[PDB]
Length: 227
Length: 227
Image (cartoon, rainbow over all chains, first blue to last red; front, side, top):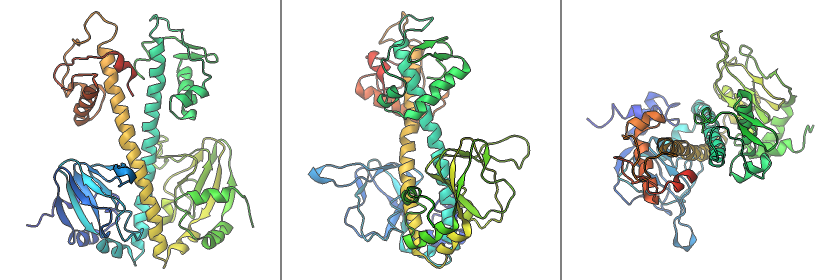
């Protein structure tokens, strides 16, 4: 009658709970407690002894720090289905170094650090399994970033060309930019190497020709797709 | 005894060699051999017994699989200053599960799996330390995805507004063609929950109306600039 039965599925997808066996998963949930917070509610203050890490189910919780001057400086924002402040465990930190707070009515789980760290201690095969899935998941995240960051790169590139190509539609050949390839990549606040991979890709397909800074557009109808 | 001077300092920056003690690293470097490959060179095949993980310093190495025996399906792409196939070390598996080939001339480090496991056994603090630097890196990568994925979505929202209302004989405040909350969601292939949020943020700056029903653009010049 106590929760359970449906919650185990929410954690079974997370990286920190995958390596754990059904027996160890229930052993950690036994010490856990459901926490409900409202708008402007603090999770843990900067100075309180570290004894538990949290797992957000739904909502938005900010961490940030209490920087000097009297202003809050945001470090990272944790969203749904993601754990935060879990690194404070195996770091052996006695107290919290951040003041967590929820902007919107959020619901979180409170897992004890003493009931999690001790389970990892001894019987290393577990820590070995934890490092296994924790790494394979860290490589898929970088792979996604490599693709997502590339999409934003392919975006600005074409966008910066269309804004100056909007001068006499049909046959676009008037391209300014007193810059020399690489140099313009540093101004657009984007990776220098990516610009030499996107422009060259358009040349291979047969859309945009390159003749040293001199950019000529063959068809504007075939550029509206990727922009 | 020494193979390189700068190459040894590059490992210190990585998360899998930082927590390791200099004394333990010296014994680990003695078993490792420097590897130099060119274009179209294979690191490890999909069948041979696994006994070493690799660390890439410069270049790019693809993996893909060949077990279904049909097409070269890519699994993960690794770049410079990143380790690949290190998860095979933890998961006591006798042989590799995937292939490996470098598309561009790359230099690699061949660290033995047995030499690293011996440093993990018995010792509990070392294992937890590795997880500490590994978890903190995950937070830094995930936070970047929450921004990049949002940027890729926002730019698309500002793109469909330009295509729907461009150099036409309509009206700035009166946009042609009605728009819903589920219709555009399929035009840009984005979450339906994010679409309503983007329209709200841009509506606060003075670009749109801030409502989903009927689009009434006040500033068309501010749209072409976007993020």
